[PDB]
Every structure is written in structure tokens, then in C-alpha cells.
Image: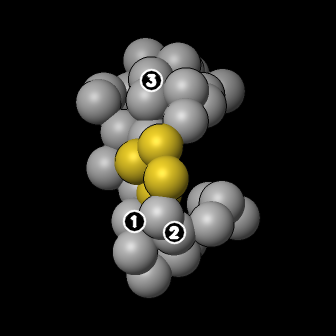
Amino acid sequence: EVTCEPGTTFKDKCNTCRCGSDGKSAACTRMACPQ
């Protein structure tokens, strides 16, 4: 559930996350946050 705005990047969870351009979807470098 990504509620970020599409058009930017931020260090969320345990890895970056370039907010996609559609919303509710980011790239993120990886996934090391088992939360």
C-alpha cells in the first residue's frame, strides 16, 4: 500500500523507493524490511 506521490524518490522501509508515476507503486532499490 504505497500512499506516496508519483514524481520523487525517498528512503522508506529498508530500501529507497522511487515513487512510480502512477501512484501506489514504487521501484525501491531492494526489500530488506521484513515488517
User: Can residue 1 be seen here?
Assistant: no
Q: Please indicate whether residue 22 sits to the left or right of residue 1 in the image.
A: left
| Residue indicated by mark 2 | 6
**Element assignment for label 1:** loop
**Identity of the amino acid at label 3?**
Asn
| Residue 32 rendering spot, x and y as whole percentages | 43, 17
| Residue 34 rendering spot, x and y as whole percentages | 55, 22
Q: Earlier in the sequence, mark 3 or mark 2?
A: 2
Q: Please indicate whether residue 8 sits to the left or right of residue 35 in the image.
A: left
Residue located 36% across and 39% down the image? 28
**Identity of the amino acid at label 2?**
Pro
In this rendering, is residue 9 above or below 8?
A: above
Quarter occupied by residue 20: bottom left
Spatial distance from mark 1 to mark 2, Cα to Cα? 5 Å
| Residue 7 rendering spot, x and y as whole percentages | 48, 64
Mark nearer the viewer, 3 or 1: 1
Q: Earlier in the sequence, mark 3 or mark 1?
A: 3
Q: Residues within 10 Å of mark 1 (few under 14, many from 20)?
A: some
| Residue indicated by mark 1 | 20
